[PDB]
Image (cartoon, rainbow over all chains, first blue to last red; front, side, top):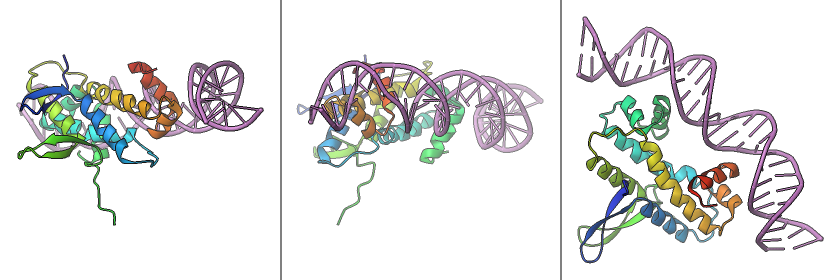
Length: 91
Length: 98
DNA sequence: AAATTTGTTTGTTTTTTGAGCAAATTT
DNA sequence: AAATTTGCTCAAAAAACAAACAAATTT
């Protein structure tokens, strides 16, 4: 059904899958909960950055550091990959 | 004084630990363990679109949640997300959420 | 009655892109 | 020895943009 899921455990010690989107939801819920009233400036180019670093780190781990297949997997350009690596400093 | 808070820890997701103790680990790891498992129960398939798949998993809620928090007001959400109002409407239309 | 926010468009800039290429590196 | 992947440059096509509004809606 859903390809992107994380394990969870309920009180009765049952491990159990759940969509990733359900964490992100929680993630944020909590963020907002936190700041009472403090304007939020850059929420998009934040969460992105907290989701690209792992995607990158991991779809390189999986390709043995082959930037070319790396890109083919991610469906984006050999170039823009080198950029995104520079951005988080990985290349 | 203000204790430091790393970015790792600015977006967190509660988890149970080795001493069934409730700790608070970065979203990062969710995205991390999510892809680990996506590879595991994969094998050999042509995977040409991995970026977009992740993205459309992360954009949906970000929008889902930001809109609920501005009780419908785009102009804010857009300003709050640090993105052009046009491109907000674009993204919305993509997932519904109109 | 204001004032804001919506729904459009019109043009510019910033980003992504393919397609080349020598040099380096893996097979 | 051969195939490939890097690191770069170019130009082209595409996505994001800010600035303008009238019409709609909310303060």
